[PDB]
Amino acid sequence: MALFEDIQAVIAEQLNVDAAQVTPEAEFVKDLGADSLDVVELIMALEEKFGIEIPDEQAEKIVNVGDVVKYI
Amino acid sequence: HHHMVSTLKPLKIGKHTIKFPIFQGGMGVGISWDELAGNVAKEGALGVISAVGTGYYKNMRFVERIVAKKPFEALNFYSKKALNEIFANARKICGNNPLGANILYAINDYGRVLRDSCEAGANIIITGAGLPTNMPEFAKDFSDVALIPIISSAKALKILCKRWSDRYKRIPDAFIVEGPLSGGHQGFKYEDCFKEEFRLENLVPKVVEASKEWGNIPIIAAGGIWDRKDIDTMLSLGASGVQMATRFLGTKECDAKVYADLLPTLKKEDILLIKSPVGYPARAINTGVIKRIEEGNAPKIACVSNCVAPCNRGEEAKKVGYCIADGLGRSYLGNREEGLYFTGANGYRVDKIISVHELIKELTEG
Ligand SMILES: Cc1cc2nc3c(=O)[nH]c(=O)nc-3n(C[C@H](O)[C@H](O)[C@H](O)COP(=O)(O)O)c2cc1C
Ligand SMILES: *P(=O)(O)OCC(C)(C)[C@@H](O)C(=O)NCCC(=O)NCCSC(=O)CCCCCCC
Ligand code: SF4
């Protein structure tokens, strides 16, 4: 819960969307309006604030915010 | 009247040098294979073998499973056996001159095809259709192969240089900047395309500027470059080289033989920007599948090859109207009613089909 809101605030700030609509089912591209460049940036932004790597082979599998949350 | 020597300077990319600063852009399916890229390399530019949909090579000669007369799954569509043969046949013509391999990042089995491409003998990997953030991961056994992403903005350069250095302490040996006049898929805002800001004469200064901050990465301009005058324009704007596809699409050595019949008839009114399962706009010729869709006569969509990941096996193909693996595959096979055909914006200017040698002469003389 503490983790989910921290990474919620980061997604909302990166993609310029309301935190209230950054829900576990929300897809970054379909639902939150981000392109490829936005997602890579977001992945880089998460890596810093949490000191992990998320190799591309998992980033290809995350798709929505809830999957990102679990990986962390 | 005699052939005349160039004042163009040789171009060096990573460990490899080409006599003219010219890439022949990769073109799938079966468009820039052995004949086209081998002869380009023979003539002193970069020949670039497209590695997408190679299972179609020699009418699926090298596939091991066929379903609906189409290569079944990425394992067969991106055939290691076929790709090695094309490199084998390309080296017949060009010897050990440098050959690129082109691989969309969108495809399934991306990593496998890059190592198949290195193992086939490629000297340079070229990757667009996506932001290839992990490209050195798959090339790690092949420190001689240069890696060249395709980008359409300075932002993409900055992003990729940061990831590759963070992760690998490596930087791309070159970047191809592709403008909105290009053939195939666009690196551009679905909407934008004709805005003044995105014009290639404007991108190249911006990308070269950004490239200075990372050790002066060589920037290759592509999209709408027609003749030596266009070449000189791009070089004067900071580019180290140009990539060109439509002019080579109109040569005899083009491996997709249907294009020699099609291009002399092509009119500007039949070049159109369409939707694609890959997820990017594509510049296509209003013929083949594109006519069959508007007629209501379009072939059936049943994902057999599973060429690209963004499609989710029919979901995007059914919504756009066509399977791009099947449509490009049929074109290589001569199917004019229901093949898919691409071109750059300059394709209507292709009036006569000439040879690679004659094209190379036009572009480099003086
Ligand atoms: C028929 C055709 C197929 C293409 N296929 C690919 C491809 O498979 N991979 C790629 O990176 N670019 C592809 N392109 C883009 C070219 O490699 C090149 O970047 C662009 O066409 C250059 O612009 P020009 O055609 O105006 O010279 C294709 C272009 C054409 C015309
Ligand atoms: P993201 O949304 O995925 O955003 C990525 C982005 C912005 C498009 C970049 O990768 C970028 O700047 N790209 C330039 C890539 C290219 O412009 N071009 C190479 C495209 S591959 C191609 O043109 C056609 C392929 C034809 C054959 C299809 C075979 C199945
Ligand atoms: S249905 Fe989609 S994934 Fe399958 S071959 Fe066609 S374009 Fe590729």
Image (cartoon, coloured by chain):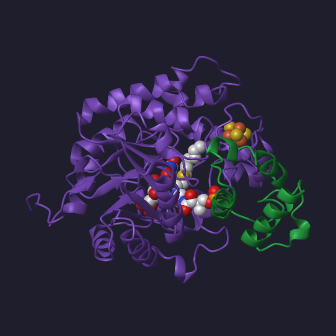
Name the spot of residue B289 as percent of width and height, x first. 67, 47
Name the spot of residue B312 as percent of width and height, x first. 76, 42
Q: Nearer the viewer, residue B74 or A10?
A: A10
Identity of the residue drawn at 60% across and 26% down:
B75
Is B7 situated above or below B139?
below
Q: Nearer the viewer, residue B196 or B295?
A: B196
Q: Which chain is green?
A: A
Identity of the residue drawn at 31% across and 38% down:
B38
Is B8 situated above or below B77?
below
Name the spot of residue A41 as percent of width and height, x first. 63, 63
Q: Nearer the viewer, residue B293 or B97?
A: B97
Quadrant holding the N terminus of chain B: bottom left
Residue A43, quarter of picture: bottom right
Which corner quadrant of the figure contains ligand 3? Answer: top right
Name the spot of residue B313 as percent of width and height, x first. 75, 39
Residue B86 makes an appearance in the image: no
Residue B326, quarter of picture: top right
Residue B190, quarter of picture: bottom right
Residue B141 makes an appearance in the image: yes
Identity of the residue drawn at 43% across and 57% down:
B246
Is B120 situated above or below B128?
above
Q: Nearer the viewer, residue B302 or B204?
A: B204
What color does chain B have in the rendering? purple
Q: Report the residue that reaches farthest toward the left.
A: B2
Q: In the figure, is residue A51 to the left or right of B212?
A: right
Quadrant holding the C terminus of chain B: bottom left
Q: In the figure, is residue B52 to the left or right of B288?
A: left
